[PDB]
Amino acid sequence: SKVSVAPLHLESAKEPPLNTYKPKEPFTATIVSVESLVGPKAPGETCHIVIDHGGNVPYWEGQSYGVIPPGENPKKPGAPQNVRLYSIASTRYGDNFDGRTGSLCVRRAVYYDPETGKEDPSKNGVCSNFLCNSKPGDKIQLTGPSGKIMLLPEEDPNATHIMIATGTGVAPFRGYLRRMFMEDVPNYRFGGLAWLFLGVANSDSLLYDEEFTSYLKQYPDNFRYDKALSREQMYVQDKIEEYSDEIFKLLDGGAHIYFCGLKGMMPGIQDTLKKVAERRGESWDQKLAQLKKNKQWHVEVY
Ligand SMILES: Cc1cc2nc3c(=O)[nH]c(=O)nc-3n(C[C@H](O)[C@H](O)[C@H](O)COP(=O)(O)OP(=O)(O)OC[C@H]3O[C@@H](n4cnc5c(N)ncnc54)[C@H](O)[C@@H]3O)c2cc1C
Ligand code: NA
Image 1 (tube, rainbow, N blue to C red):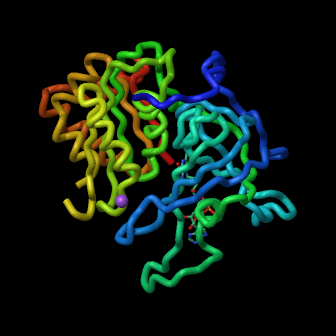
Image 2 (tube, rainbow, N blue to C red):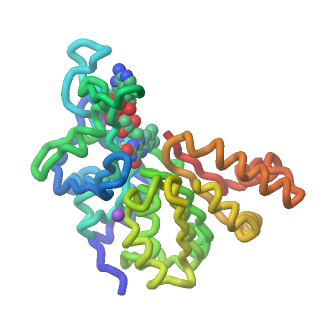
């Protein structure tokens, strides 16, 4: 049942690519598809964008692409816009299983007057709206890839990976999980435990839910999946708390734990972890220092 992927030479590099393309000479990639991931009751749109890089901008799971949106830099006359980074949401083979495309999971940044709700196109986020407004055949200026914080540690194919996402923070984990479960990668046969926790606003805001639910049926002994709906139920930290003893035992046994999404997710998580630890009679500060020393703690928030 795993999906054949090509070309297998993408497994041969011993280090991830970094800064293959730079802002002064980006790679001009082409949009394959853009689709909304969310339903009518979601508070805003999050879209899935598939980009054809032609095999010219390969990457490893957990890396980011840069995108240079069109127009002048408003702060620097006659200069290009600054790069915006996006976590790649695909495996290195991409959604067409061919090594030619990568995907992004992009939240539209829209401004609303806090009193009146009135819009202002000069205040929306440039790159996120550029991307979600894109159509097949459109060109995008791609840079990178960049980043190493979120590379998947593969030395132990039986490791445990606890993945904590809010919103678009799911992106690297979609790539991890396809590599672990979906794709036929003969040199990486995952036999550990992957546990995804996802916090979103409501059921219509869920991202890739059918995919993750399918892994529960395909790999019941290797995958777990828990959701938190803040407006319906509940934050992701409340779900960690529900499983606190299991999680703390996995951490003590060597599990990796990952956090990705908007940085506002982290204070509540740190508060919860401190309280859980205290109830167990442990110091969260001591435990976190040990997790960081042991290279178990991975955070990419923005
Ligand atoms: C490592 C990394 C990974 C990331 N991964 C993702 C990802 O997977 N998905 C994702 O969606 N994002 C991700 N981001 C965030 C992304 O890089 C962008 O910051 C985000 O998309 C907003 O960029 P933008 O160009 O749309 O908005 P910008 O044009 O940069 O505007 C920034 C914000 O300012 C607001 N604003 C602009 N004008 C005003 C004004 N006058 N008054 C009030 N508000 C105003 C905009 O509405 C917006 O909210 C990631 C960031 C990092 C660093
Ligand atoms: Na949905």
